[PDB]
Image 1 (tube, rainbow, N blue to C red):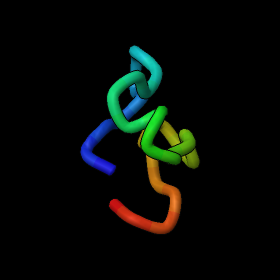
Image 2: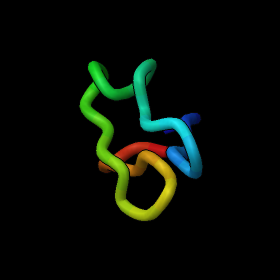
Image 3: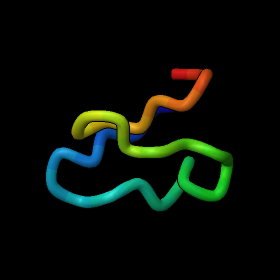
Length: 30
């Protein structure tokens, strides 16, 4: 997922099924 929650949490890919694994959204897909 093209979303890194370094400061701000995922909002775009959040509804796509991506969770913050480690300051970046990575759930199956990048």
